[PDB]
Amino acid sequence: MEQRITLKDYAMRFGQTKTAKDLGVQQSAINKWIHAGRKIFLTINADGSVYAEEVKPDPSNKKTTA
Picture 1 (cartoon, rainbow, N blue to C red):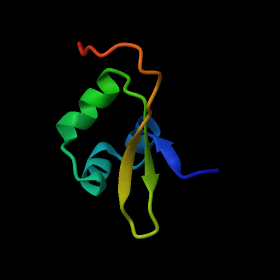
Picture 2: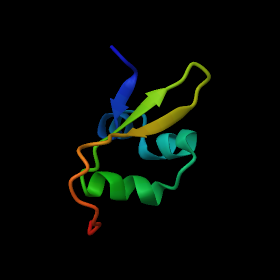
Picture 3: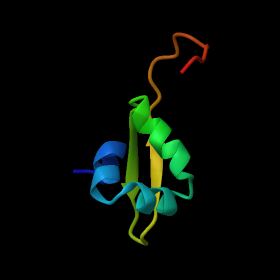
Picture 4: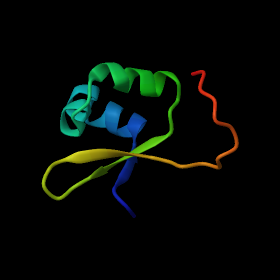
């Protein structure tokens, strides 16, 4: 299986700080990601880094609310 874990699993597993640190983001964005149930998958590298991959659903609308 691929190494694309869920933001929830990795967050509750490794933590919210350890993730935001390896990703290079702010803990503020992480909380907002799970707060709104943002579907994401962070992949673990062989060097010790991690990058959050975003899905690309079907382009139906072009608006943004929350």
